[PDB]
Length: 138
Length: 138
Ligand SMILES: [Ca+2]
Ligand SMILES: [Ca+2]
Image 1 (cartoon, rainbow over the protein chains, first blue to last red):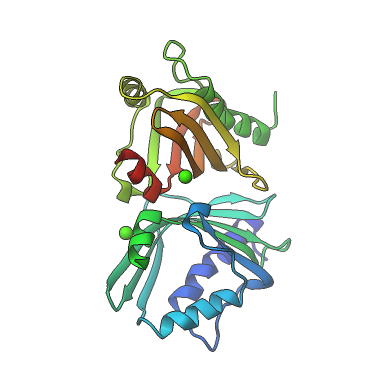
Image 2: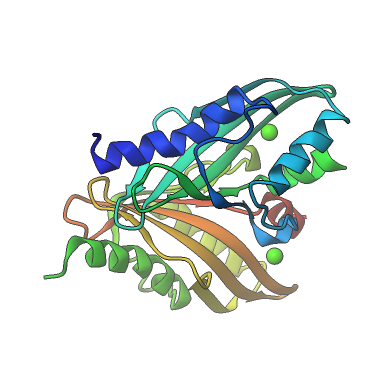
């Protein structure tokens, strides 16, 4: 038994742990069956995706580029913003990944929503550096 | 005498109310003397600004363009994320403003920090649409 504030942090942090050790056989862990990944802002044009649509994007990316050394860490000096009543955790993050065409690195704001028990992830929302992601896509 | 959650939301909401009715004579309200404005991400290239450096940009923008009908509203469906222990409030916002070169409008993630009493703003951090802001400046 953990305090609800800490348990919300462990559950939200597992999202980044699952990405660092990602494997198609195991896949996505720590989420509900109806979890949704939201990409902010709406001007970027990315629609919301379920636990199965993100997998299809993962698989399609494996056939185009190689992805090695995923790394996620909080920005130094930032603290987890936790709202126990709404079951929400806010993170200020940086993501690192080695692609075939060099290095991927950007700065993000993550918003996690858990279930009532605070054990599984219900919603994951991330605000994205639009100028860099548009440049990476093009 | 309000509950801290409602008091933190009102103190953080005053930032948008002060901007909608901004007047150089009245100036910035609801902030401590050492309040710092932060513009995320760091890739955008905007240094942190004090209470007087933000006023200087306001003055410098009045000589080049005209700003009218400043509007701000929470994105429908979003709720204020409040961390009472950290004195932090998170918003999902849209800002509207009319300039000389058309309409300004974009989506934001706002993070506010208050004093121990929860009556004044100590820090305001905003993550912006980098692809749209670099288009507006150019
Ligand atoms: Ca970058
Ligand atoms: Ca826009």
